[PDB]
Image: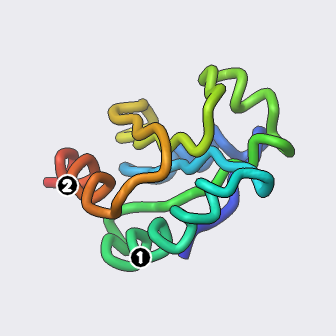
Amino acid sequence: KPIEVTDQNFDETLGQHPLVLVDFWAEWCAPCRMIAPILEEIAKEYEGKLLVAKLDVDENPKTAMRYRVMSIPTVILFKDGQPVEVLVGAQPKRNYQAKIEKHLP
């Protein structure tokens, strides 16, 4: 299931997994609540091939600033530690699947 990442372990997490989907979210954002369960299904479907991580922008402002994430929810896919895809806003699960499978062997 989705793990939590912070400004402290953000880099360490990205360097240990070949493919990581990071959800930049906030508890005061309705759209974020909507994709939460969707990201959970994504976590299961791609277990072993994808790590789903969640970055709470209110608790990790420097990480959000780092990537200039001004609108949430925003999901960024990292491959070998580098960003490769971005999905802005609450969206159907198929949109995430498409960008994930685009980078899977």
Amino acid carrying mark 1 in the image: Glu
- Could you say which quadrant of the image residue 85 lies in? top left
Q: Nearer the viewer, residue 10 or 89?
A: 89
Viewport quadrant of the N terminus: bottom right
Q: Is residue 21 left or right of residue 95?
A: right
- Count up the numbered dots: 2
Horizontal and vertical percent position of residue 29: 71, 51
Regarding mark 2 in the picture, which secondary structure is present there? Answer: helix
Regarding mark 1 in the picture, which secondary structure is present there? Answer: helix
Q: Nearer the viewer, residue 64 or 30?
A: 30
Q: Residues within 10 Å of mark 2 (few under 14, many from 20)?
A: few
Q: Is residue 33 above or below residue 71?
A: below
The residue that appears at 34% across and 32% down in the rendered structure is 84
Q: Which residue is mark 2?
A: 101
Q: Is residue 48 above or below residue 103?
A: below
Q: Which residue is mark 1?
A: 41
Q: Nearer the viewer, residue 18 or 33?
A: 33
The residue that appears at 67% across and 22% down in the rendered structure is 66
Q: Is residue 92 left or right of residue 66?
A: left
Horizontal and vertical percent position of residue 21: 46, 51
Horizontal and vertical percent position of residue 53: 57, 57
